Image (spheres, rainbow, N blue to C red):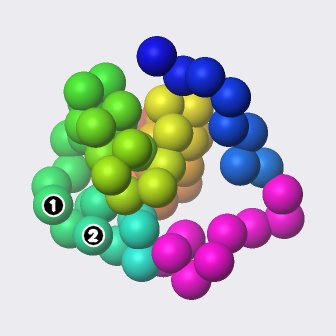
Amino acid sequence: KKEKSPKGKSSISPQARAFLEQVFRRKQSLNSKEKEEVAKKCGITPLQVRVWFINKRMRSK
């Protein structure tokens, strides 16, 4: 749904690596479902899961 959450201010708590840690730990191919399902349970967002995982999971592009 995405209501209102930029989450763009310098950086995030240790969760940055922790949240992503368990995220990339659960699997690798985080799809639109996992990107949204993972972003809401891990602490990311539909906009982050893509850009965030890009650098934290640069698979292709």
Q: Residue at point 68% right, 37% down?
A: 5
C-alpha gap between disc 1 and disc 2: 6 Å
Q: Is residue 51 left or right of residue 36?
A: right
Residue 38: percent from left, percent from top: 31, 46
Q: Residue at point 49% right, 49% down?
A: 44
Name which quarter of the figure residue 6 lies in: top right
Q: Is residue 12 magenta?
A: yes
Q: Are marks 1 and 2 in contact (CB under 8 Å)?
A: yes
Q: Is residue 41 magenta?
A: no
Q: Return the residue found at the far bottom.
A: 14
Residue 35: percent from left, percent from top: 34, 36
Residue annotated with mark 1: 26
Q: Nearer the viewer, residue 52 or 9?
A: 9
Q: Return the residue found at the far left.
A: 27
Image mark for residue 53: none
Residue 4: percent from left, percent from top: 68, 28
Q: Which residues are magenta?
A: 9-17
Q: Residue at point 84% right, 65% down?
A: 10
Q: Is residue 48 left or right of residue 32?
A: right
Can you see residue 12?
A: yes
Helix, strand or loop status at disc 1 = helix
Q: Is residue 30 left or right of residue 10?
A: left
Can you see residue 54?
A: no
Helix, strand or loop status at disc 2 = helix
Q: Nearer the viewer, residue 22 or 42?
A: 42
Q: Nearer the viewer, residue 57 or 17?
A: 17
Q: Residue at point 51% right, 39% down?
A: 45
Mark 2 residue crowding within 10 angstroms, few (<14) / some (14–19) / many (20+):
few
For the residue marked with disc 1, what is the amino acid?
A: Arg
Image mark for residue 22: 2
Name which quarter of the figure residue 30 lies in: top left
- Magenta residues, dominant SS class: loop
